[PDB]
Amino acid sequence: SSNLTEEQIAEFKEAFALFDKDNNGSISSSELATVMRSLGLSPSEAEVNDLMNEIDVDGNHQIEFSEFLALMSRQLKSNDSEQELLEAFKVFDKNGDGLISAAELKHVLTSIGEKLTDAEVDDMLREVSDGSGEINIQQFAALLSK
Image 1 (cartoon, rainbow, N blue to C red):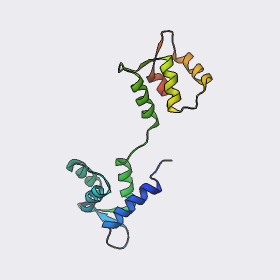
Image 2: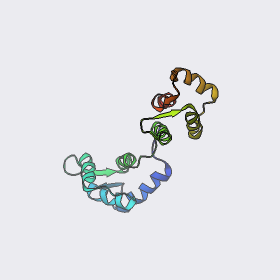
Image 3: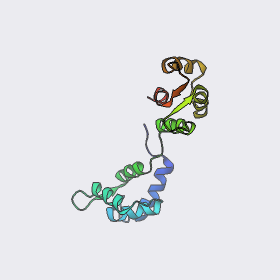
């Protein structure tokens, strides 16, 4: 599973309780945009309208700490193992397509910290390597992630 953490949920609770001046834990959409600016965000007027549209169903809607944390998690995203692998292989590939020598491929697998000894890369190189010299990170990146 993957959800917000106590540290992240603690920060939203402080900003949410600040505007929450009733007796439960809900804020109006008019204060939602302001609560995000105080938490450390700055969505353009276009992003605020889209978010307020999903919340405002009949013109009025009280955002609860549950729906608020969900919307914040989508905007405060910061986790991607697959994308992280493609990013590293991109830096090693000066060309731009994604081609590197077996040497650069072994170093990238070690830097990422992948639990794959030489035996694993050997069995994967036989199915990936065809007989040229430079391997593509696209197929190798999928073997490590997908």
